[PDB]
View 1 (cartoon, rainbow, N blue to C red):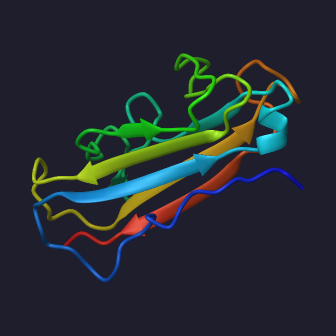
View 2: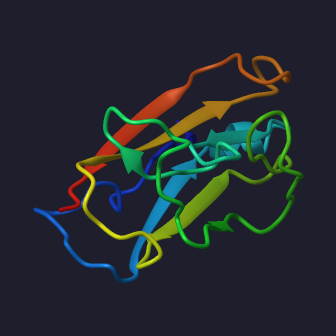
Length: 145
């Protein structure tokens, strides 16, 4: 009932973009309100060098992908935590990870379609090691021309 999980609409682009300019794309991972309040931590991760969020060519490697300029992380202010266990997590009482990146002029556009994936999971209730419960997935193709 009181659990919300979502990787938000800033996923995917329109038809095509040939601009080398700031195209800010704000992605989000939401976790169960009641489970967070139950003493459980939120899990969210992406594809960056630190597994946070990354835009990389479809069929390509994340190490060849393009960095999100300056990724920012927003959340529900209350009980935070350190980025460990292979992902970003807060303390119980919080269920939010807003990962907003920007495909910037820092990369000259020309490669084919990009893929952006965000993953979600609830830990601590199930197990608190690294990966154990329901991992959600959302991948979006960004058309760069």
